[PDB]
Image 1 (cartoon, rainbow, N blue to C red):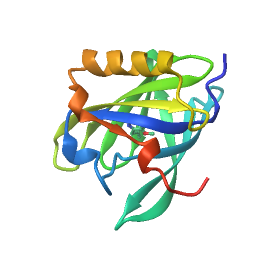
Image 2: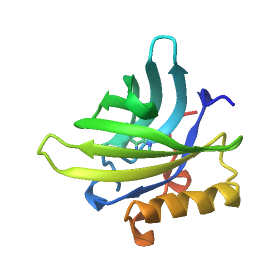
Image 3: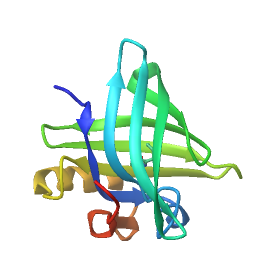
Length: 148
Ligand SMILES: COc1nccnc1CC(C)C
């Protein structure tokens, strides 16, 4: 079961809508994730937009207790890969921004643009359990026009 490889964002849910709309820090268009267990690190490559233009990021996080990872980006983040199937990853992340506000978010990742409903239903359930309403879910594939 390998989690490392190409991963593209299809949907994101957030307890704070200010963090996921147009040009927001967490409207994240993932491209790949590499879990380096020997060195207890994780490598994340994704695009985001500022001023409506795509910008690329390559971050390095550190493995912590309970299969969680810490990474700095728009404040401090602690995330976990809550679910993994042969076709998807569901990530749960808690962000504390520079102003100190806390936000919980969820993201569904896949190998391309063709979503499997089985994975999507699990994403909606994880999102609900985290107290995030359905109306707070954004369709990221629909918004991802950044480079491959
Ligand atoms: C790829 O990023 C994400 N994917 C889903 C929800 N939130 C984020 C923010 C980080 C840094 C994990």
